[PDB]
Length: 124
Image (cartoon, rainbow, N blue to C red):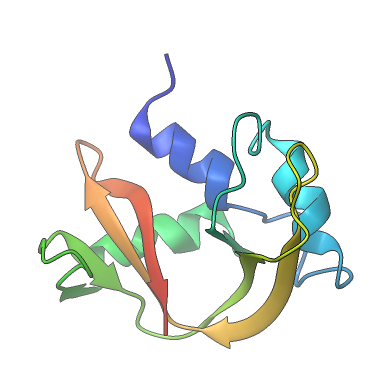
């Protein structure tokens, strides 16, 4: 069975590239980890940084999560990210997404032992 931290890495890490490679990056990447196996996730963000740099955020600025919980953390500085937002013309199995590359702070929810990221909360 997939652990929370594993699902996190699967859904949000893309250390192999520095930025979105084309305006079609989201379309390609959301197909790739069986990520759209059942549905077209409304919003999904990819972090173009080492896992070490992202797991490090759980020891940075403690913030409230958008849902009210207080196990969230904001990165000290900015990170290379790509925001994937589902668009109009989506027709499962052909999910359609807008690719948005930006240099931003990330907010993640952390848990466990080791204390790691398990959900992507926001990019600010």
